[PDB]
Amino acid sequence: MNTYLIDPRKNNDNSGERFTVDAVDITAAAKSAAQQILGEEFEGLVYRETGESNGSGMFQAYHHLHGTNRTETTVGYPFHVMELLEH
Image (cartoon, rainbow, N blue to C red):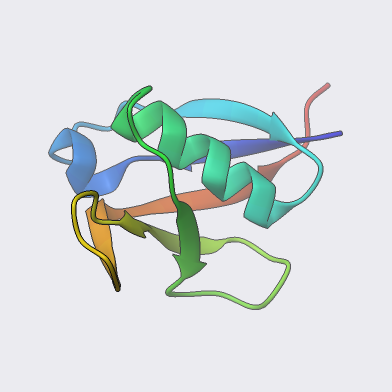
C-alpha cells in the first residue's frame, strides 16, 4: 500500500485544501480521490492529463451519463495526484 497526496484544484476553487488517500498504485489512487472529491453517488473512472505513466499528474474523472444508452462524459474538474512518502 502507498499514500498519495490529492489536490482537488478547481473542484474546491483552488482553496489549497488537500488530503491523502491510500492505494496500491497511482490509477487506483486517482479513482479513490475522485470518489472523495465527487461524493458517494459518483461511479466512474479516471484518465490522465499530465505526467508520466505510473507517476504523479493531473487526472480527470468520467462516467456513463445515466439515462442514456451510450458514451462517457467527464465529471468535475481535473485534480492532482502525487506520490507521498510518510514517516
